[PDB]
Image (cartoon, rainbow, N blue to C red):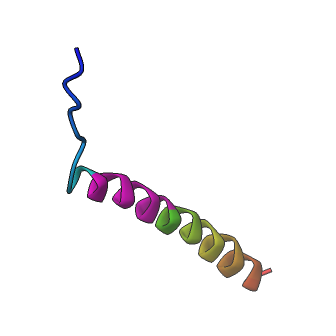
Amino acid sequence: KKNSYSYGWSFYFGALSFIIAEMVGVLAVHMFIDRHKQLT
């Protein structure tokens, strides 16, 4: 106990990549629904 292990560097690049990938995936659906609403 009291080892003070650190989650450190580029592990956070995975956590950042999650947010970036999810912000990608939501915008795709905006493009879908807007692109389909154009042909309505």
Q: Is residue 14 left or right of residue 27?
A: left
Q: Is residue 16 magenta?
A: yes
Q: Secondary structure of the magenta portion, mostly?
A: helix
Q: Residue at x 40, y 54 (%)?
A: 18
> Measured from the top left, where is residue 9 in percent x and y?
20, 55
Residue closest to the eye, 33 or 7 = 7
Outermost residue on the top side: it is 1
Q: Is residue 14 left or right of residue 40?
A: left
Q: Is residue 37 above or below residue 28?
A: below
Outermost residue on the right side: it is 40
Q: Residue at x 35, y 60 (%)?
A: 17
Q: Quadrant of the N terminus?
A: top left
Q: Is residue 33 magenta?
A: no
Q: Residue at x 52, y 65 (%)?
A: 23
Q: Residue at x 66, y 80 (%)?
A: 35
Residue closest to the eye, 9 or 26 = 9
Outermost residue on the front side: it is 2
> Measured from the top left, where is residue 5 in percent x and y?
20, 33
Q: Is residue 5 above or below residue 37?
A: above
Q: Image quadrant of residue 37?
A: bottom right
Q: Is residue 30 above or below residue 16?
A: below
> Measured from the top left, where is residue 39 in percent x and y?
73, 83
**Which span is picked out in magenta?**
12-22
